[PDB]
Image (cartoon, coloured by chain):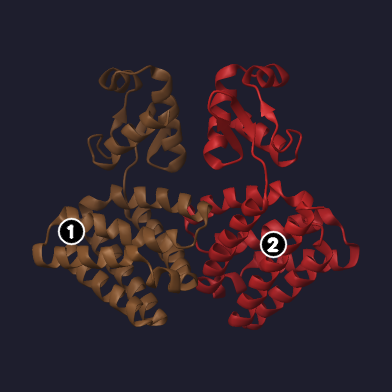
Chain colours: A red, B brown
Amino acid sequence: RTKVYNLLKEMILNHELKLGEKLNVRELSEKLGISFTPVRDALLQLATEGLVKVVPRVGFFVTDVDEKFIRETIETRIMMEVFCLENYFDKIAGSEELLEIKGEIDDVEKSAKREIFDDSDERLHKLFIRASGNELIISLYEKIWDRIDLVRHLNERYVVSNREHKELIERIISGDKEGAIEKLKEHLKNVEAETIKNLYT
Amino acid sequence: RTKVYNLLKEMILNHELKLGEKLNVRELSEKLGISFTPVRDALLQLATEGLVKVVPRVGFFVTDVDEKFIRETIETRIMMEVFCLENYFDKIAGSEELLEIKGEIDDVEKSAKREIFDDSDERLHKLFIRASGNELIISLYEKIWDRIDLVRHLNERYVVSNREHKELIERIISGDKEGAIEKLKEHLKNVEAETIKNLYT
């Protein structure tokens, strides 16, 4: 149930199962060599998360992504990341993980290696959330991050995002709370706009 | 389906199925008069929501409630409700729904009827979230409200909460965003403390 959930989610997030694609439990079970029941269980789990849609009298489909999808994700990120950066600022600023990430970011500034960036991006934003120690918020944000991953194909600006991340960390390290928050908001709004523009290719 | 899920969730939230109680799929199916499949489907969804726990080779149980559960809910409420009240203030202030809630509050103060209070409490806090128009945040908050309903038995201070709601709404109508946010945070912290204190009675 979990192995298969994780496998099917990976296939949706990396678009092996395409946005909007019709999903058939039996096809998947045969494709994956896994019985029917845990495939169905996993699809239902994915439906409650919004990555799968269940259309009465028809069946399961991979979610479509439209402007609303992107916008709702970004507003949710603003709400959660800002709350956590504001209220757990000193914990974040003093963390060993912030310094590791800072190094990754410097590496990207030189290499423009997208893979390192992707790592650093997930790590930085999840750090802000993890610092709360609130398992409920952490678990909710894991699913919000899935929505971000789903639209990664539209998020081309990584070189400029990396500069934004570099500056954000500098503000955090210096103690500039309000400046850090403003930079985080600017970054998220810039991502929103770029992501949406690329939706319309 | 969702109907079965709603019935079972309702039985948890009203403590027909007690906190920590072992849930038997066979027994539940027979009680509700339905096939096993949708009962199992519903329990698995409730498990992903945190209202049910799955214990390996043992089975399903209603969640227990402890201090962490309460605290994590309350922090998440502060996060979401403050963000929506801050960013959608004028929309909330001008809504007809705020005026109806205002009237229910006066009913409660005169009458101290709990049932009217519980309606007003859900309506006021959900109004703040609904004003965002963000369906993702609205859908997440629906499940956070389930966690609030689960601990209603610990939340005795409704007469004083109602007076806090009265002041909060007066601050919204007066146009004092900052004062309204302060009062909302105070109210939520006061609910937290007393719900926790009543946990250990």
Q: Is residue A7 visible?
A: yes
Query: Residue placed farthest to the left in the image?
Result: B111
User: Which of these two is toward me, B17 or B106?
Assistant: B106
What residue sits right under mark 1 in the picture?
Answer: B156
Residue at disc 1, secondary structure: loop
What residue sits right under mark 2 in the picture?
Answer: A192
- Residue B77: which disc? none
- The span from disc 1 to disc 2 (Cα, nearest Å) is 43 Å
Work out whether A81 lies above or below A122: below
Instruction: Specify the amino acid type for callout 2.
Output: Glu
Say which chain tag 1 marks: B
Residue at disc 2, secondary structure: helix
Report the number of numbered marks: 2
Instruction: Specify the amino acid type for callout 1.
Output: Glu
Residue A183 left/right relative to A141: right
Residue B56 quadrant: top left
